[PDB]
Image: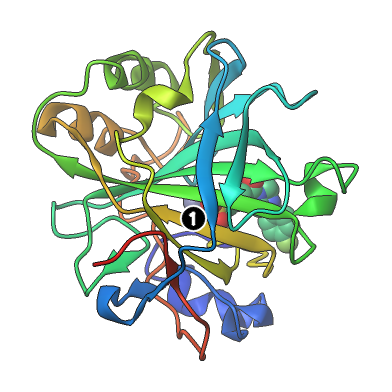
Amino acid sequence: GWGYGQDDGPSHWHKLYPIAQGDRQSPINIISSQAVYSPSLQPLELSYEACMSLSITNNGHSVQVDFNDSDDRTVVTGGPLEGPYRLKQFHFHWGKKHDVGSEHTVDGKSFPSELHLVHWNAKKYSTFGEAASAPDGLAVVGVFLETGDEHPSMNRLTDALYMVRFKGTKAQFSCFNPKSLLPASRHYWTYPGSLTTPPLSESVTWIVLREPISISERQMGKFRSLLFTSEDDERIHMVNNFRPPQPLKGRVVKASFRA
Ligand SMILES: NS(=O)(=O)c1ccc(C(=O)N2CCN(Cc3ccc(F)cc3)CC2)cc1
Ligand SMILES: [Zn+2]
């Protein structure tokens, strides 16, 4: 019912999910000079185990790696979070050129891709779905990707894309440590927001890392080789699967650092 094409793209989502015009929608354009330095925030800690990954899937909207979230082994804690949130899955948003692809932008600048590590408040809610509807239910850590030098650990992931090039396909993806996709800095911007895809619920505490990671153009190209379409269909490459910046509506963006 929704996608990233000319007829079902982000500009039309509100026709189906009215909350798309809400007061805490994501993503947003981060004006670094207007972010509020908040030294009162606790250190952001991403405590990830190496073998919690389950599979890699092309769900028609992105490529997603799902995790075992039975306990609090792989969690994010600190920063603006009151407690630990368990990692459920990570996925990406990307474009067709280096000038576009990320959802969040910084001072008007977009990156070729953005990684989203999705976590939920399992201590408070029974299911991820239950959490995805509550204001304090989710915590998504966003990491910008820039193109430059090849990323060693990313190779395992980009090499796996061929087997999930078609929509609705999946493959086993064991022992991939999402910590390998994090930058050396834990500085970030945070603000109250929403899921960036339908149902667009305003249940996400966003934590956007300041430092991007880089992958090579070859690796980025592997993402663009994915398809929005199934095997027996006219091929349409999965690109520009991002939602543009939404109105801030008076929300305060906090920063764990001084610009
Ligand atoms: N990019 S993001 O904001 O980081 C993000 C994070 C989590 C999710 C996520 O797992 N699904 C949300 C969507 N739902 C499907 C859905 C769609 C429409 C509905 F009305 C209900 C449920 C599956 C779970 C999606 C996007
Ligand atoms: Zn996302």
Quarter that holds the C terminus = bottom left
Q: Position of residue 119 (x, y in %)?
A: 64, 42
Is 106 left, or right, of 160 in this rendering?
left
- Report the residue at 63% width, 26% height from top: 74
Q: Nearer the viewer, residue 4 or 151?
A: 151
- Report the residue at 55% width, 50% height from top: 140
- Report the residue at 33% width, 72% height from top: 30
Q: Position of residue 245 (x, y in %)?
A: 38, 74
The mark tally for this picture is 1
Q: Can residue 223 be seen in the rendering of this structure?
A: yes
Q: Can residue 58 be seen in the rendering of this structure?
A: no
Q: Nearer the viewer, residue 146 or 169?
A: 146
Q: Residue furthest front?
A: 40
The residue type indicated by label 1 comes to Ile
Q: Nearer the viewer, residue 42 or 130?
A: 42
Above or below, 31 relative to 151: below
Q: Nearer the viewer, residue 236 or 213?
A: 213
Above or below, 7 relative to 250: above
- Report the residue at 47% width, 39% height from top: 91
Query: In the picture, residue 127 is in which quadrant?
Result: top right
Q: Position of residue 150 (x, y in %)?
A: 14, 24
Residue on which disc 1 sits? 207
Quarter that holds the N terminus = bottom right
Is the C-beta of the residue carrying label 1 under 8 Å from the nearest atom of ligand 1? Answer: no
Q: Residue furthest bottom?
A: 250
* Dot 1 crowding, Cα within 10 Å, few <14, some 14–19, many 20+: many
Q: Position of residue 221 (x, y in %)?
A: 19, 33
Circle 1 SS class: strand
Above or below, 195 relative to 246: above
